[PDB]
Image (tube, rainbow over all chains, first blue to last red; front, side, top):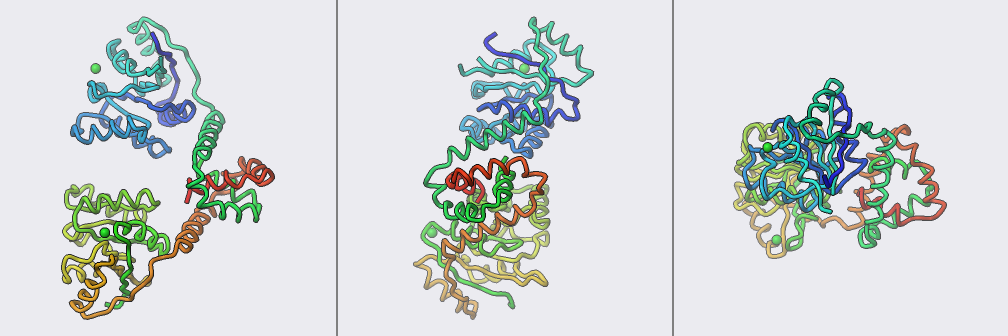
Length: 207
Length: 209
Ligand SMILES: [Cl-]
Ligand SMILES: [Cl-]
């Protein structure tokens, strides 16, 4: 197909962090995350938002209105992560994403292909998280799918440090003279004190 | 009535920033801002979010489950600002606060008293702040006749004051980023000093203040 696919090992324990960490590392414009229940999608978006990820759920107990808003902040980039379910995830109103994550594995080819088909705006990415005792299941899914999936380890604690670190860098770079000029004088105060610790700490708040 | 009452001038449609600015300067443990309708409490809440205020809307459409959460966050400190209508602000689940702010003059004078009774926490004292436009310099006089009391007339806060406040607030969260957490970035900081990159630091403070 026109997209890439990887299979990432993660104990259901640290399956959330892995998700987050993978997100920091690639940090794509739009990520679509599928899970098995409405509780999960909600449960999940909650853990993400906590870790510094603009994630919001997408399910059935959603009034078409809150669901246009959700898909609105997602299309505008306000929301970067969409934790969804196969059904809420259906329509014409469903925008395309850059990365697809099967937080829990799909039992059918049509399933995998309905979720995975939501990636590509030019080719895209697809990631599969699996617990240790989920091996065969992935082996079965592969057979249903017809293609095999590369086994890629999870992102390194340092891999993530440097990813966050480089996005923080790109952010400051985006700030404009009109907004940062308001603060130059305070910047001077810090230079004048020249205590490397204060600034490191300010950076620690952001990163 | 022991607490303090004040009338503070707001520009036409700049009541938000004056509110925020008043928040930053006063930094009260809990604040309650009264509005006329829920779309109001809705808008001022989101507004206060932008400007760096942990605030939440409290209107009557809220389920009793949301109601409880919201008010739990507020009593516990997770929410510093509660934005309510008069109807929604009814109940013994509402806690006493440090600051009551009437976003607009109370529709009526009995309303004032009822809003204002919310302020005042033992060992902390309490304060009322009335926000008035320019057409309303008359209305306040009236409210003071109807209530038979004078509100101190208090200048809003000067941009300096505001900035110094955000700043002290910020250095405050910093006083607890253990060395453990920030060490990795000191060299980079050092280079920013050496290469005199004040703008980067400036962009940094923008993203934080
Ligand atoms: Cl389906
Ligand atoms: Cl106005």
